View 1: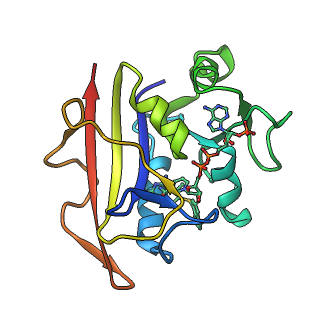
View 2 (view 1 turned 120 degrees about the vertical axis):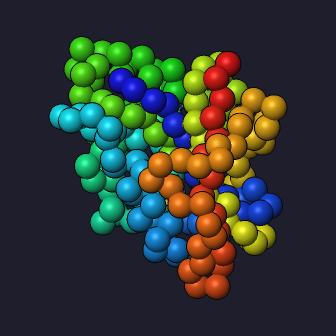
View 3 (view 1 turned 30 degrees about the vertical axis):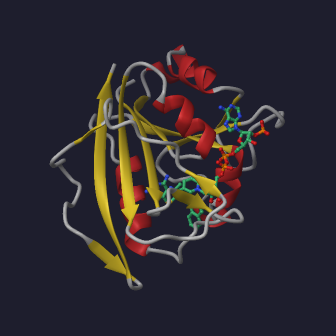
Length: 186
Ligand SMILES: NC(=O)C1=CN([C@@H]2O[C@H](COP(=O)(O)OP(=O)(O)OC[C@H]3O[C@@H](n4cnc5c(N)ncnc54)[C@H](OP(=O)(O)O)[C@@H]3O)[C@@H](O)[C@H]2O)C=CC1
Ligand SMILES: Cc1c(Sc2cccc3ccccc23)sc2nc(N)nc(N)c12
């Protein structure tokens, strides 16, 4: 198992979701970017694992579920088995990560990507260790009911470049946004 990473897109007022969808209209290349980053494994013969909350799972369009070319793991304490189309089910972030050190998964998994939502991000972000955040800054306010947790800039350094990540501003449907990578090691 290699890197642990969170990936998110967030509005200027820290919003990530609204009524079970994104706060903004669909941004095709943003979804492409998320797909490219989470799918691509820096090793041969391995796959990345994506970990997500139950509400995130059911926010993804059925036709993109499971997220293809990745091992999909859902967090829930109410479900008794993985949802239709998912691969694994865990009861805590720790268990999901323990599960990666299993004989079963140990040698099939390259990167682990936490793909949301709020509570999964917060726990991963406050836990000691080496962690990167891939943050798409959506450069407007949007009405939101679910928020990204505070990024403590004392611990998380914004990297001045990162391979395979564009630095300049993008725009789709009249909404500008930018890609950022943060790293901590504590
Ligand atoms: N990048 C972005 O902009 C992203 C946006 N989104 C959007 O954000 C919102 C997601 O919402 P959010 O409410 O934060 O939901 P989550 O995806 O975190 O789902 C919450 C449910 O997941 C289970 N869960 C969460 N964490 C854990 C855990 N550590 N261990 C066991 N179970 C856990 C609980 O389910 P149970 O009650 O069954 O125990 C909880 O009720 C949606 O609107 C979605 O579209 C989602 C991802 C990224
Ligand atoms: C899970 C996710 C997605 S998938 C998704 C998540 C929530 C609602 C969606 C609605 C339509 C299509 C896809 C949806 S896009 C995206 N972008 C970044 N930078 N980070 C993420 N974690 C996601």
